[PDB]
Length: 157
Image 1 (cartoon, rainbow, N blue to C red):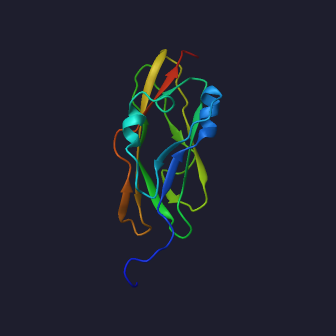
Image 2: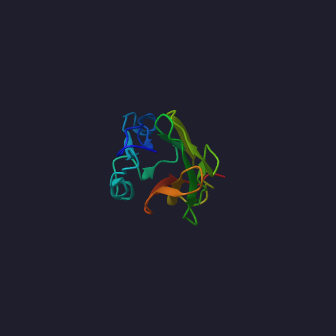
Image 3: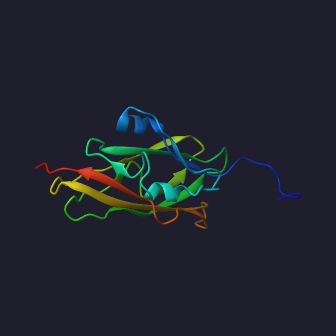
């Protein structure tokens, strides 16, 4: 509470970390989603056929995502959407964290697990959308609705 606009630490960062992409094709590819809350138009590429984001093979059980705040700025998050969309190639996506929480200044990994029901062979889809608020509950950052992935399963029972 202050002079004209001060200079303090940055806003929320969220990227899909490259370590996971190695497990996808032995090649390493990061994808920056949210940089200082100033989110890139990443959602076009995310839902478009990208080299690495949509199509996931049966072999990948889980993906990783990585996020953080800057120094004193812990953002609060809550998962609006995280669910499958298929019928035959049906699965249920899961997260390595609670459905709500905070984004910490500490670069922290969030695994996303994809147990498939192993019934029909093909490619199922799943939706994700997450909102972000300050600790009082005031919404401030919101994922745009299009973040959909595609997980290739085969029959196994």
